[PDB]
Length: 191
Length: 191
Ligand SMILES: C/C(=C\COP(=O)(O)OP(=O)(O)O)CO
Ligand SMILES: C/C(=C\COP(=O)(O)OP(=O)(O)O)CO
Image 1 (cartoon, each protein chain N blue to C red):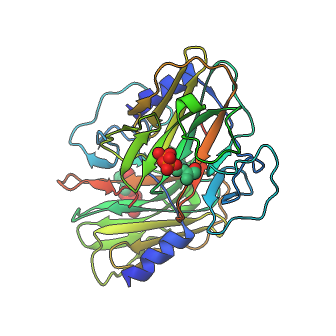
Image 2: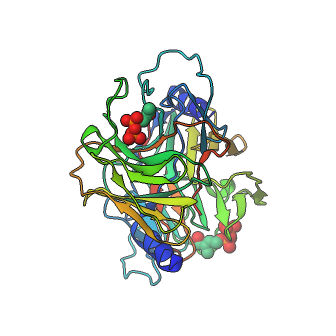
Image 3: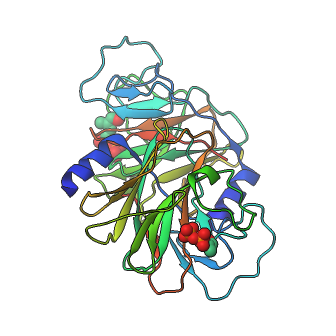
């Protein structure tokens, strides 16, 4: 069940060793020293406007992108009451206010808002019903087949899969947090 | 106060999301479908050889181990008249009969026998005197300080702290039940 999940993911997808890129992180984000976790600060840091940095979206990326193959990583979201995670195109508009995070705008993400509302960030947003709140989420990228999927990485249940896409840009792991709370997002070691 | 215990656990220790590993579970144990609970059976299962499995001790482990950091989880023991819980080293002699569960053998555990006799499984065993019987037990690991502690998770009260170890191996949550009875051991998910 969980076991079947682990066997399936290990057979089919390459483990990506994701580390967060402080240079991309909106100034309201604190990336941990080990670059595995990200937290939202109360006050923004005073950081330069280098082209890589998100200036509007409360986002940070992985250091490395994907251009082909099947890849997965897992993110511990624990009890944090707001988070959205997935992948985004390298050429997302990092410097424009109010760009909706949607596949059309180079984002493939899902998560949680207001403690209990699960969504996939489609346009319009898709509401999800998950019998069990995930503590750890498996993100899955099949670049060739154009498929971004999410699983509960502990009990192996399927969370969501985006419609078929035809990727024309490299894809980054992306992480977004809006609220001030205690629990971090953490990229966990993967089998 | 339970309030102080709540604040303390939440400030200092990362909440471990513990799921029982059925491949480790001695064949006389039955792990629930959600792998949050374990019960002792009257008859063993007939299973294929597995290196991970406890052959002698009536034990099951968590799926994940700890190699650094401060971690806690909380176990519902209910009115069950016999149980022992804690952590053990990854390299405990799983396959060997008659190994005493003690710190020298890779185990740091405490619990209940015969309804009313609480013990820490030191060598010798140290008898505990608990003003009230717990129904939920908080297990606390601080890997750097070598500190394994047990608390009454409802009212915050201290149950037992082992002499500080110098851990040189990854640590698993471990769970042992000997006796036949209706109340399972249950891991309460992250609050
Ligand atoms: C302010 C902000 C994001 C909120 O965006 P939205 O208000 O469009 O809502 P959502 O559906 O969650 O994307 C910065 O990332
Ligand atoms: C039979 C058994 C465990 C009990 O071992 P022991 O009989 O040595 O007693 P204890 O002091 O509770 O460890 C299988 O796990």
